Amino acid sequence: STPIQQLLEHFLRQLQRKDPHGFFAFPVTDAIAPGYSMIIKHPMDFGTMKDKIVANEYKSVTEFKADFKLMCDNAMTYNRPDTVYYKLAKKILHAGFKMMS
Ligand SMILES: COc1ccc(-c2cn(C)c(=O)c3cc(C(=O)N4CCN(S(C)(=O)=O)CC4)sc23)cc1OC
């Protein structure tokens, strides 16, 4: 595994620590979130990000950060502001970008 893979694995570990319930661990299913796939055109989650690192699909830190932001933006689009998912998405978006510097 390459230097970028090693760095991204480090960032991903640190980001996932901010989601102890694992709300962002796996793709959101329509069973858990009614109509999700018909509202969110480009789903993303931490599990998919892990698989993309292992497959060496991220060629820059910029691309990784864009998937992280996509994940958070999707949650802030689908969920109303008063939900646990919206609130956590906003919190980890800002904290995660600060952590990655
Ligand atoms: C199995 O554990 C979980 C895994 C995923 C979700 C989940 C993740 N994310 C990121 C979501 O955006 C999300 C939305 C959920 C949902 O069904 N909602 C929240 C938003 N409202 S809304 C549109 O009325 O604001 C509809 C119901 S479940 C879920 C929730 C889980 O249980 C606590």
Image (cartoon, grey):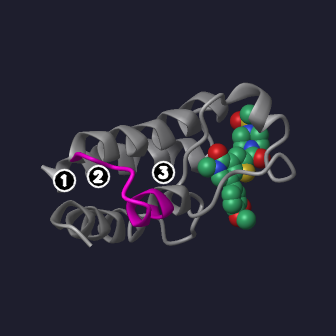
The kind of residue tagged 1 is Met
Q: Quadrant of residue 16?
A: bottom left
Q: Residue at x 21, y 67 (%)?
A: 2
Asked if 72 appears above or below 13 in the picture, the reply is: above
The 10 Å Cα crowd at callout 2, few under 14, some 14 to 19, many 20 or more, is: many
Which of discs 1 and 3 lies nearer the camera? The answer is: 1
Asked if 31 appears above or below 1 in the picture, the reply is: above
Residue behind mark 3: 88
Q: Where residue 45 sits in the image (x, y, percent)? A: 54, 53
| In front of the other: 53 or 67 | 53
The 10 Å Cα crowd at callout 1, few under 14, some 14 to 19, many 20 or more, is: some
Highlighted range, magenta: 50-60
Residue behind mark 2: 96
Is residue 82 inside the magenta stretch? Answer: no
Kindly identify which numbered label has been placed on residue 100. Answer: 1
The kind of residue tagged 2 is Gly
Tell me if 93 is positioned left or right of 89 in this view.
left
In three-dimensional space, the C-alpha distance between marks 2 and 3, rounded to whole angstroms, equals 11 Å
Tell me if 84 is positioned left or right of 5 in this view.
right
Mark 2 vs 3, N-terminal side: 3
Tell me if 35 is positioned left or right of 90 in this view.
right
Give the secondary structure at mark 2.
Answer: helix
The 10 Å Cα crowd at callout 3, few under 14, some 14 to 19, many 20 or more, is: some
**Could you tell me if the residues under marks 1 and 2 are in contact, i.e. CB atoms within 8 Å?**
yes
Q: Where residue 70 sits in the image (x, y, percent)? A: 46, 36
Q: Residue at x 81, y 53 (%)?
A: 32
Quadrant holding the N terminus: bottom left
Is residue 56 inside the magenta stretch? Answer: yes
Asked if 13 appears above or below 90 in the picture, the reply is: below
**Could you tell me if the residues under marks 2 and 3 are in contact, i.e. CB atoms within 8 Å?**
no
Mark 1 vs 3, N-terminal side: 3
In three-dimensional space, the C-alpha distance between marks 1 and 3, rounded to whole angstroms, equals 18 Å
